[PDB]
Structures are given as structure tokens and as C-alpha cells.
Image (cartoon, coloured by chain):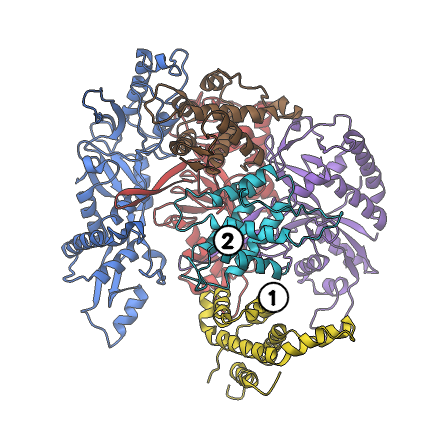
Chain colours: A yellow, B cyan, C blue, D red, E brown, F purple
């Protein structure tokens, strides 16, 4: 992740928000573990949403609302909103950091395909992976095996 | 099975072209039930009767239910395009004419489960792509 | 055999009406156009009709007694002339003379003429304001419909219960609680098992000194007054036949224009911010009286616009 | 103690929807068995209905049925509900309003089920039912049959005119078998029972939708005829003793009427559940 | 009861041959009601009453509703034409004579379940085939 | 005394989960074999179910199945549980309620497995099954066959694949093969059995979750038909003979019923395991 932006700030706030604090014992906003598998499984559709221009925010909100459409998900609207905001910020940072770099790497006919592929970073996919890894870290800290 | 990104892209294009999604990214809220019921009906009653039922235009339905068959046709045409052409390929790749209705097309060219498989994948793609929009 | 229906000596009335009606006898011939109009076909159908219309029902019938034991105390009403028609749209027709040309609603197992609970529920809901669906087609008639039915229902509720004022929102909530067991928005109220309003099937209970089935005529004279009218013969429930209406109704609690459950309403009662002004109660007895008044006003069955299916107190 | 057999007496017209789309006359069809293609109640529907009846006793439901789907901690259920299979179906006749119709294949299925599961009163019922089936097959000699045990119901028409009832002597029906199967019982061949219980012969009820007194929709619903009998098996799975006893008493008490299926508000699926009495 | 595509092909050819669906690929709108009513009549009244009612020609109806019986006859003949030799041992694989009353045929052939299933399937196929096309 | 063959008789509907995320109509699919794609039971699930039945006998479980997942000491399992493959499945018929359906390829795989593994009574079964398979192939000669061995069952229809059963009168079916494969046996071509065992023709059940009478969720489950037969191999890896004898006697006891799969609270996946009898 790049610390020169709001994605790092939002990532820190999300971690602090959804990590259980045992030292206290009043409460923290609850966590939905099914969002972790949704991010992994629906990654291609999320990439399609992210690559959409000037409609990605509404599309992301609609996707998360329409996938988590049950009465039990009324409590996790804050988590869904935070995930959407962080994902959009990370996609913007990744395109602004990597689009020109990738398009100059792609047509640099000195490197073979293997090193080009190891050098070419997909912005939307990297943002999805970052959000997924952050959610997995939250779950790993939160989950105990009593 | 996983989600085919290309089929979802075809679903997006077909949903926009067949006038299910309005300009402010919205649909009349009966179409999600239409797609889910189409999948269930294809499983439970067979391809031809389900296609005839959902392709009928003289229906007392809330909205234009026959548009989902147009979306199905567009998705199937798009995926039959970019089918690889090798002499070992079981796929037809012939494009369904816009003159033809889906039911007559399956009637006169229907001897293989290729259409059933393509329709199942197209219905799944429609279901997953419609979740990206809002219901009026 | 011919009278006193009972379970030991009878033919299933539904079987007689639907499967045995067009039995192929050695010399009947209603296949041909000539034979459809013949006197032999008319005599055949006359004998079948006499067999169908010859059954009476005793008040102390084990069938109806079992119905009373299973579904509860019946609401007893009487049919007045011309009678009661139900299931009129069921296909029973071949093109012959002397034949019954309208369907009749018969219970499958017992054969007794009956009014299905869905018919009773719909007939009762029809006079409640929120029975017409909000649709594009129905949008032009929706407001007048609701206004008329809401005034009617308000008068009925004030007459039956000891409620002095009822609001339009209260009527909406009460109707949705009775018929949908839900909030007008579509939400669900956590209800107990005994807090469900059930509309069982009505049954014929007593014929007294006569039979419970008869034959009736409608003769539609056409738009052309110079052409011969066509007589249509159908089957009706005789006048002065007792109809048992079985319901399972609960008490509906209304607090601040919303419908409350029993535990909800007791918890609200124990609260110190409780007022009797916005608490309303209509009991199962009062609900049954309201349903009785609706039934005595509009009747039940088919062709109710022309007097068929009107009911009277025992 | 472990396995018990319960019989569902239907007090009204049952509709348990399969949900499959039918494009013929009947829009809504009833659930059928995967193997025998006879009307049945899926065990999930049975469990849901009985859980709804007992929902007021939270402790009993939690012990016997399990935890609610919303609870953070999930508790497995202890008692096991097996699907309700069709035992007897009423058939309309000219000599009597309705007869109790059962097939030899249904009897064989019940005998096999009792042998496999070892319900409490299984031994006597299996012995006498096997005797009945052997007598019926010896008399039938491979032909079609419709056997009545009351001599007064001779020549009765079992719905269709092609099926007429004969009374064979030498074949006794025990009073306990009459209690289990039904009064005015007719023993049908598999062909006849398949004909009488297929989609074209099961009862259908016509329904329409009215908007300001004018018809908007129209559909037909297949229903299971009133007073039909279905049997299911219940195994207690190390459930607590007094909770099990309360479940057994409340379930089998005369005043218990349980709603199974659809269209509850219009009186459809109301049933009485009784336990297999000692022979 | 699944309607195969071959049965629907038989239904379309029969509906065209009996001059219900014109060369314009349209049909009189009352025939859909005729087919639905026949389907309901078979299950409520019975095969014999329904066929007698829909087979007579001296009716005061808008259109020739006796042609649905001819369509039924053609569909049943086409189905019986494809019965295998093993089917012919149990199933009557004999062409309905044509110019013969269908009610007379069913009366003479007992009331076997075979004819009831055949007519039910053929009526459903006719319904679906009519839904393939457009009302006039 | 090692490597004996066991046959699973399914007394109820069976659902062993696949763990596959199906975006489609049927969300819950059953476990299918890797090579043949026929429905199967994974050896892990079979071992878990049999361990759960025997968990009251701690010493037998420890010696045969191994240590518990939480034991401080890890004891390897001594018995080897092979996966269970589909042998016979009930297909719907008209003359009879159902027929037991097996393909020629299923028989070939059974013969191959018996040859490879040296089952206890493998030799006679291999000889007679090879005779039967060769006779069937001689009678079919590259055609789409469907053969019943009871002359009364001639012309029975398989409703899903609209074909009728022929009787090859000059092919014998031995009583032990009847016991193994099942009563009312039809042996079909591979394509017929593949069509009958695919996702579109296996029974699919509709289920919902009702929150205060309002539908909260809806999903479709596919199940293995009741009375289906599956076979698996058990190898006795240097296990104590007395614990082995207790395990085998308890497993093949008629009163033993084992639950394999999901939806235990409803009557799903209840099975009887029998040993291969001498021919």
C-alpha cells in the first residue's frame, strides 16, 4: 500500500474500527466474515466495477447492497461502506501510480513475457487483493478458537 | 465453478442494448425474478417450454418479460463470437439471426446440448450482472 | 340410498356430477348432433339430475359433527331464494339437452357441497378498502373504491365493537392484520400460533325437510329480440339450507395505529407511558359478528349481483 | 424407544408445493416422492410445521429441534424427522361417499420400512401385514384387483368405471389394521393406484383473482384429498426424556391440529398426528 | 410430464395443417382460450365430455373450435408414428383413421390411460405452440 | 481376511455436500466421483460417519480409526476406508414403482476393482459378472440397450429417458447377483445411465426459510434417490482381530443404521451397510 494518500488512512481506520478490543472486555462495530469470501470469489466482477468510469461508486454500492440483501446485513452497512470507500481510493491510487508505467513496460521489446508479467501490476486487482488481505488480518486478529 | 468475466461483460452489454437497464442504471425490479425463474424453469420443465413461456409477448406480465430472451440471444451470439476455430471443436459458432426467434431456432437447430449449456451460463451471467444495478 | 346422504349409503355427489354424469350407456348417443337433441338423451340426463337432486342432509350428521369437532363452533346462516351457486366456472358441458351446463363446487372426499375458504376470504376482503391492488390499470378506480369501502368498514366496526373512533390508518392496519397477518408495508409481526386468522371451508349442514340441491334456469335473450333464447340449466343449493361457516379468529390489538402482538401489548400496558386513548381491541367474537354482517350484506358465491347466494340468520 | 411411527390424518385439503413450474393445466402441483412418485411431505416441511407448533416452548424447541437460524451459536437438533409417505387416499364411489384406497406396493413399502427402522410396535404389524399381502397375492394370481373387506361394498366403482370392487373371503382384515389404514378400505393393484393418484386424477381446485369484482388471474391448484393418511418415522437422538415425553403427549393429544403445507389462512393443511397404537 | 421439442414440432405442423395459424404466422385470438378451456375440461369433466363438447360443429362460437380436435388428432397420429416396436407391444401404435370421430375412437378403444396421457400431452404441446406465435 | 467389500443400502434421501460454489439454480450439489462423475461418498465422510456411530466404544475407535483430533498422543488409523461408488439407482417405471438401474460401465468398473483389490469373495463374483457382461454385450451388439431379467417387467418404461425395457430371455441372472445389484434390475447403456444420473434428472428439492411466515431465503438441493446402492472396500491393516470382529459384526447387524452426509435432523442419508456374501 502507498502511504502518500487517503487509502493508508482509511486502512488504519478500518483496522482500528473492526478489531475487537479484549482489554475493555463497551462494544465495537461487528464484522461479517462472509465479505472476505465475497471479495475473493467476486473479484472479477469487482474488477469490472472498478474499471468503469464515473459510475463505479454507485455500482459498487449497488453490488454490495444486492449481494447482501438479507435482514442480517442491516447491521453491516458501515462495514460495506468502509470497504467500498477504501477499494475506490486504492483503485484511484493504483491507476495514478501504475497506468503509464504498465503501458511503457508492455511495449518495451527488450524484456521477455515472463519478466513483463512479473512487472505488470493490475490496479483494480491489486486493490481487491489489498482489501482482501486487510479483511483477513482483521479476521485473524478477531477470531479465537474457544 | 467460477464466474466468467467475459460472460459478465457480455451480460452488461446485452442488458444495456436490450433496454432493461435505463440510462440512470436502473431496472423495473421484476427482471431479477424473471432471470431467477428462467433458470429454475429451464431446470424443472425443459429448455423449449421455458423459452416459449418467457419469450411470449401476449402475456399479462408486469413488464416486458420477453426482453430477457433478447439478452440471452445477445449473450449467446457474443460468446459464439470469439469461439476458437479448430477442427476438434464441438461448438457450432454460427450466429443466431436477429430475424429468428429463440424458440424456432432451438426447434430447427436443437439436436445438441450446446444450446442448453450456453443458455445456462448466459442465465447465470445475467443473474450476476444484474446485481450491479438498482431496482426502481 | 336416495335420501339421507350419510357415509354408509350414498354416492359421491362430486363423482355423480363430474365422472358418472356422461357415462356411456348402451343406447344413449349424445355424440351425434341428432342424438344430442333427442328425447333419449334428455331422459338420460333427467334421470341423472334426479339422482343428484334426491339427497337430503340431517342436522345430526356424523360428517358435519366431525366438521364441528375439528374446525370449531360453526357460524350458522340460511340460504334464501333463489339459492347459492359456487364453482360456476368449472367446465361441465357437452352440448346436450337437459344437461347441467354450469360447474358446482363439491368436496372431493365427502361430496358435500361446500364454499372453499378462499372464496369466503375473498368475499370478506372485497368490502375492505385495501383489497384492490395498486396497479397502473387499477389506479383510476383506486381512490373511490378505498373511500367507499373505508366508510362502510368504519360504520361496521363502530356498530360491532365498542370503539368510538377508528382512523383510516387503523382500518388499513386492521385489514392487513386480519387477512395478511402483516404490516401494510409488508413487514411481519411476531405472532403466536393462536394469533392467526383462518378461513376454513363452509359446508352445507342441514337441509331440514327438503333436499340440499336443486336445478335452476337462466335464459339469456340475445341482443336480437327476434331470435330464440337459449335455456341454460345449472345446479344450485336449495333455499332454506343451513350453511356452516368455520373460522379461527384471534383478538387484534391496535396501539398508536399499529397492530401489536399479545406480549407486545402486555409490555405496553405495563409501561407508564400508556394511554387508553390510542389502544383499541376487537375480539374474535366481534370479528365474527363483523364477518356475519358483511356476509348478510353482500352474500357469497356466484351471480350475487342477481340475488344468488344471499344468507339469513337461523 | 428410538424409532416411532406416526400417522398423519388430514382434516382438510393438503397442499405441499413442490415449486416446480408446470405449463399444463395445473399451475401449482404437490410434492411427490423421488422414488415411488406418490404424494409426500418432505421432512423439512414436517420439521418446520412441528417447530412452528411448539415455538412457544423455547426450551423444548431448542433441545429437540435445534437453534433458531438467527442465533449466533448453533445447536444441532436431537430428534430426527423422516419424510411423510402416503398411506391411504380417499377414492369416490357410487355405493359409498369415499373409500380408503391403498396399493399392494404401498403395503410392501410400509412393511420394508418397518423392518428396516424397527419402530416400537413393528413386529405384530409386520407379521399381520405380511400375512395380508401374501393372501392378497395368492388370490390375485398376477391379475388386476380391487379388494374390499366389507361385503356390502361389492361391485363399487373406484372412481373410474373400469375399476370395480370384489369382496374376497378367506382374507381377514384385523381391527388394528383397519385402525391403521382406514374404514371402508379397498386394496388396489399398483396400476389402479397409479392411475388414481396421478396428476390427471388428483383433486384440483380452481382459483381466480378479482379486481373490483372482475377476474384478473386464474389458476388451478392440485391438492391432497381430505382425510388422507400419511406415515412418517421419528427417531429420538439422545434427546432429554421429559422434553421428549411432552413432545409425544402434545403431538398425539386429541385436541392438537397441526398445519402442514401452504394456504394456511384458507384452511388447507390442517392435520391430526397419531402414534402407532399397540396391536 | 416434459414436452419434448418433437411434440412441439408436431403441434406446430398440425396447427398449420388445420388452418389455425395462417401464412402470416398469426392465429385468431379465441383459440388460446379454446385450448386452455379444453385443458381444464379434460381434468375436470373428463376426456369424453371435453372431446364431445369441442368436437361438435353446430356451435354458436366465433371461430371453428372443432379444429383443435383435428390438431389433437394430427399430434396423436404423429406421436404414434414414432412408437418403437417395443412400445407397440403395450401401446396401441395404430393411426387414428381420420374422418373418424375422435370421441367415437376413444369410446371404442375403452377409456385407456394411454389416450388420456396422449391427449393431455398433445393439448399442452398445442398450448405452447400457440404461444410461439401471435394473436391476430 | 483383508480387503472385504461392503454394500451401502440407502434407506432415505442422501445429500453429501460437494463444497462447490455453484452460481446457478442448484446451490447444494452432491458429491461426484472424479473419473466417472457418478455420485459417490468420499472416504473421509464414510470414515467420519462410521466413527460417529462407534464413538461410544472408545477402545474400538482408538484401535481401528486412530486418535481423536485433539489427543496429545497421535495414533495412526489401522483400517483403510475406500470411497463408495454408485452401484444401483432407482429409476421411475410404470409397471412397477421403480427399477434398479445399473450401467454396463458400472459393472465393468466393479469387475476391474474386484480384480485389482482381491475382495474376499471376489473370484466367483468376477466370473459370473464377466459372464453376464459378455452376454449383455453379445445381445446388444453396439446398440442402446435396456434389459430386464424378469419376464413380467418387459416393456417397463423409464420415464426420464423415454425408453422401454426388453427381456433378453437367454441371459441368466443368478440369485446372488440379484442380491448384490438389487431387485427389479435393469441394465442400461452408458448413455442412458449418464442421462439418468446427471444434474437435470437427479431429484431436486425446493427449500425455504420462513421468518414469521414470510419467505426469507430460497434454495434448491439435489439428493441421491432413496434405496440407492453404493459399494466400497475395507482393508484391514494389521488391526486386532477381536476389535475387527466386533466392528464387522456391529456394522453388518440388521439393526445398525448409519447416517452419512448432511441434513441429519431431517431424514437424510440413513444407510444400511452389508458385507459381500459368498456366491
Q: Nearer the viewer, residue E123 or C201?
A: E123
Q: Nearer the viewer, mark 1 or mark 2?
A: 1
Please report, as a chain letter, where disc 1 is located.
A
Are the residues tagged 1 and 2 within 8 Å (C-beta)?
A: no
Name the residue at 25% across, 64% down: C254
Query: Is any part of residue C79 visible from this angle?
Result: no
Q: How many callouts does the rendering have?
A: 2
Task: Please indicate whether residue C44 sits to the left or right of residue C305 in the image.
Answer: right
Q: Provide residue D275's location: percent of width, then percent of height.
A: 47, 47
Q: Provide residue A69's location: percent of width, then percent of height.
A: 47, 65
Secondary structure of the residue carrying numbered label 1: helix
Task: Please indicate whether residue F215 sits to the left or right of residue C266 in the image.
Answer: right
Q: Provide residue A9's location: percent of width, then percent of height.
A: 54, 86
Q: Nearer the viewer, residue B56 or C247?
A: B56
Mark 2 is surrounded, within 10 Å at the Cα level, by few (under 14), some (14 to 19) or many (20 or more) other residues, namely some
Name the residue at 48% across, 15% down: E100
Q: Which residue is mark 2?
A: B36
Query: Is any part of residue A28 visible from this angle?
Result: yes
Above or below, comparing residue D253 to residue F77 in the picture: above
Query: Which mark, by number, is residue A44?
Result: 1
Q: Provide residue C36's location: percent of width, then percent of height.
A: 34, 15
Q: Nearer the viewer, residue B117 or D70?
A: B117
The quadrant where residue A6 appears: bottom right
Secondary structure of the residue carrying numbered label 2: helix
Above or below, comparing residue F183 to residue C214 in the picture: below
Please report, as a chain letter, where disc 2 is located.
B
Mark 1–mark 2 distance (CA, rounded to whole Å): 21 Å
Mark 1 is surrounded, within 10 Å at the Cα level, by few (under 14), some (14 to 19) or many (20 or more) other residues, namely many
Amino acid at each position: 500500500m502507498s502511504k502518500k494518500g487517503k487509502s493508508y488512512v482509511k486502512f488504519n481506520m478500518l483496522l482500528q474500527k473492526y478489531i475487537l478490543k479484549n482489554k475493555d472486555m463497551q462494544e465495537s462495530e461487528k464484522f461479517l466474515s462472509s465479505v472476505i469470501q465475497m471479495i475473493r470469489a467476486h473479484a472479477e466482477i469487482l474488477q469490472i466495477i472498478l474499471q468503469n468510469e464515473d459510475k463505479r461508486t454507485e455500482m459498487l454500492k449497488n453490488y454490495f447492497d444486492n449481494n447482501f440483501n438479507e435482514s442480517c446485513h442491516l447491521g453491516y452497512t458501515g462495514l460495506f461502506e468502509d470497504i467500498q470507500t477504501l477499494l475506490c481510493l486504492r483503485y484511484q491510487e493504483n491507476i495514478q501510480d501504475y497506468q503509464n508505467r504498465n503501458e511503457i513496460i508492455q511495449q518495451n521489446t527488450i524484456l521477455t513475457s515472463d519478466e513483463k508479467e512479473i512487472l505488470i501490476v493490475s490496479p483494480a486487482m491489486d486493490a481487491i487483493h489489498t482489501i482482501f488481505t486487510a479483511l483477513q488480518f482483521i479476521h485473524f486478529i478477531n477470531y479465537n478458537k474457544d | 465453478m467460477k464466474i466468467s468475466k467475459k460472460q459478465i461483460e457480455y451480460a452488461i452489454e446485452a442488458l444495456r442494448a436490450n433496454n432493461i437497464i435505463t440510462n440512470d442504471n436502473q431496472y423495473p425490479k421484476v427482471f431479477k425474478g424473471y432471470i431467477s425463474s428462467f433458470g429454475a424453469a429451464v431446470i424443472q420443465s425443459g429448455l423449449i417450454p421455458a423459452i416459449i413461456f418467457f419469450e411470449n409477448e401476449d402475456n399479462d406480465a408486469n413488464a416486458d418479460r420477453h426482453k430477457i430472451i433478447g439478452v440471452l440471444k445477445d449473450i449467446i451470439n457474443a460468446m459464439r463470437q470469439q469461439y476458437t476455430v479448430t477442427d476438434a471443436t464441438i461448438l457450432v459458432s454460427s450466429q443466431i439471426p436477429a430475424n429468428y426467434s429463440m424458440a424456432q431456432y432451438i426447434i430447427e437447430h436443437g439436436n445438441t446440448d450446446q444450446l442448453l449449456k450456453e443458455i445456462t451460463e448466459a442465465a447465470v451471467a445475467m443473474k450476476l450482472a444484474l446485481r450491479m444495478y438498482k431496482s426502481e | 340410498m336416495p335420501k339421507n346422504y350419510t357415509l354408509q349409503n350414498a354416492s359421491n355427489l362430486g363423482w355423480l356430477f363430474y365422472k358418472d354424469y356422461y357415462r356411456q350407456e348402451p343406447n344413449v348417443d349424445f355424440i351425434s348432433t341428432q342424438g344430442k337433441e333427442s328425447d333419449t338423451t334428455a331422459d338420460f340426463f333427467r334421470k341423472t339430475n334426479q339422482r343428484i337432486t334426491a339427497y337430503q342432509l340431517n342436522s345430526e350428521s356424523p360428517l358435519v359433527a366431525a366438521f364441528n369437532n375439528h374446525f370449531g363452533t360453526p357460524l350458522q346462516l340460511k340460504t334464501i331464494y333463489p339459492g347459492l351457486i359456487t364453482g360456476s366456472g368449472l367446465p361441465h358441458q357437452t352440448g346436450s339437452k337437459g344437461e347441467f351446463k354450469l360447474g358446482f363446487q363439491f368436496d372431493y372426499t365427502t361430496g358435500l357441497p361446500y364454499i372453499p375458504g378462499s372464496s369466503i376470504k375473498g368475499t370478506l376482503r372485497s368490502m375492505f378498502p385495501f383489497s384492490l391492488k395498486d396497479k397502473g390499470s387499477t389506479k383510476r378506480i383506486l381512490p373511490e373504491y378505498r373511500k367507499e369501502r373505508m366508510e362502510y368498514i368504519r360504520d361496521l366496526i363502530i356498530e360491532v365493537t365498542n370503539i368510538n373512533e377508528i382512523s383510516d390508518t387503523e382500518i388499513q392496519a386492521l385489514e392487513y392484520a386480519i387477512f395478511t397477518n402483516s404490516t401494510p408495508s409488508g413487514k411481519t409481526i411476531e405472532f403466536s400460533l393462536e394469533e392467526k386468522d383462518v378461513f376454513y371451508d363452509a359446508f352445507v349442514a342441514d337441509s331440514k325437510d327438503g333436499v340440499m340441491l336443486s336445478d335452476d334456469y337462466i335464459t339469456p335473450h340475445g341482443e336480437n329480440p327476434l331470435k330464440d333464447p337459449k335455456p341454460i340449466l345449472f345446479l344450485k343449493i336449495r333455499p332454506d339450507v343451513t350453511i356452516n361457516f368455520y373460522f379461527k379468529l384471534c383478538t387484534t390489538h391496535l396501539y398508536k395505529e399499529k397492530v401489536c402482538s399479545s406480549k407486545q401489548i402486555e409490555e405496553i400496558k405495563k409501561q407508564n407511558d400508556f394511554s387508553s386513548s390510542d389502544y383499541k381491541m376487537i375480539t374474535a367474537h366481534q370479528k365474527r359478528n363483523l364477518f356475519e354482517k358483511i356476509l348478510l350484506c353482500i352474500g357469497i358465491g356466484a351471480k350475487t349481483n342477481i340475488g344468488y347466494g344471499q344468507l339469513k340468520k337461523l | 424407544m428410538t424409532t416411532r411411527m406416526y400417522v398423519i390424518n388430514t382434516l382438510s385439503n393438503m397442499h405441499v408445493g413442490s415449486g416446480e413450474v408446470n405449463y399444463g393445466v395445473i399451475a401449482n402441483l404437490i410434492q411427490r416422492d423421488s422414488v415411488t412418485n406418490l404424494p409426500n411431505i418432505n421432512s423439512s416441511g414436517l420439521k418446520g410445521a412441528i417447530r412452528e407448533y411448539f415455538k412457544e416452548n423455547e426450551d423444548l424447541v431448542r433441545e429437540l429441534f435445534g437453534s433458531a437460524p438467527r442465533d449466533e451459536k448453533t445447536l444441532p437438533g436431537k430428534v430426527r424427522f423422516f419424510e411423510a409417505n402416503l398411506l391411504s387416499m380417499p377414492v369416490r364411489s357410487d355405493k359409498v361417499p369415499f373409500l380408503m384406497a391403498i396399493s399392494d406396493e404401498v403395503l410392501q413399502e410400509l412393511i420394508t420400512k418397518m423392518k428396516f427402522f424397527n419402530c416400537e410396535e413393528a413386529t405384530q404389524y409386520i407379521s399381520h401385514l405380511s400375512t395380508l399381502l401374501d393372501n392378497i397375492k395368492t388370490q390375485a394370481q398376477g391379475t388386476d384387483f380391487a379388494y374390499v373387506f366389507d361385503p356390502l361394498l361389492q361391485g363399487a366403482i373406484i372412481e373410474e368405471v373400469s375399476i370395480r370392487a370384489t369382496c374376497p373371503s378367506h382374507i381377514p382384515l384385523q381391527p388394528s389394521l383397519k385402525k391403521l389404514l382406514g374404514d371402508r378400505l379397498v386394496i388396489l393393484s399398483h396400476k389402479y393406484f397409479s392411475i388414481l393418484s396421478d396428476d390427471n386424477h388428483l383433486p384440483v381446485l380452481s382459483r381466480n383473482n378479482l379486481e373490483n369484482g372482475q377476474s384478473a388471474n386464474l389458476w388451478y391448484e392440485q391438492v391432497l384429498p381430505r382425510y388422507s393418511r400419511l406415515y412418517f418415522m421419528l427417531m429420538d437422538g439422545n434427546a432429554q426424556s421429559e422434553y421428549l415425553k411432552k413432545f409425544r403427549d402434545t403431538l398425539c393429544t386429541p385436541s392438537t391440529i397441526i398445519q402442514i403445507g401452504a394456504n394456511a389462512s384458507i384452511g388447507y393443511g390442517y392435520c391430526q398426528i397419531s402414534e402407532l397404537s399397540p396391536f
